[PDB]
Length: 135
Ligand SMILES: Cc1cn([C@H]2C[C@H](OP(=O)(O)O)[C@@H](COP(=O)(O)O)O2)c(=O)[nH]c1=O
Ligand SMILES: [Ca+2]
Image 1 (cartoon, rainbow, N blue to C red):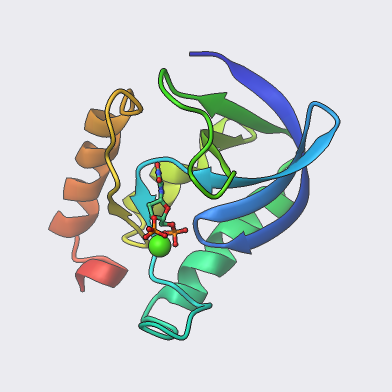
Image 2: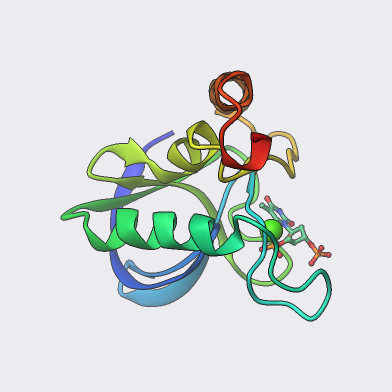
C-alpha cells in the first residue's frame, strides 16, 4: 500500500470527505468504518452522529497534510466514491474514530481489508473503555 497526497475540499460526515485527488474533486468513503449517520430520512440522526462528523471534520481541517491510501481491491464503490484509508498529518482518520468509540469496524469486503486487525484492536480497546458508542 502507498499513501498519496490529496487536498481537503470539504468534510461531509464522520465517514465521508470530499478531496481534490490528482487534480480531480472526489468523494472518499473511509474504509472499514461505520459512523452513526447524521443525514438520512431512514434511521434519521443517530446518537454520536454529530460527534463522529465533528471529529472527522476537525481532524482533516486542522491537518496540514492529508494523504489517501487505497487498499488492494477496488478503489471505488457503487456510488463512485473512492475507498481509502485517510491520513491527517500521518494519523489514520479511520483508526482515530474507531479508537474514540465514534465508529464500528464494518463493511469488511475482502481484499480491501489490509488494516482490519489494526482497526479491530482499536475497536476492542474503545469497547473495553466503554467509550461513546460503547458507553
Ligand atoms: C465502506 C464501504 C461502503 N460501501 C457501500 C455499502 C453500502 O451500500 P448501500 O447504500 O446499499 O447500503 C453503502 C454504505 O455507505 P454509507 O455508510 O456512507 O451510507 O456503501 C461499499 O460498497 N464498500 C465499502 O467499502
Ligand atoms: Ca454509515
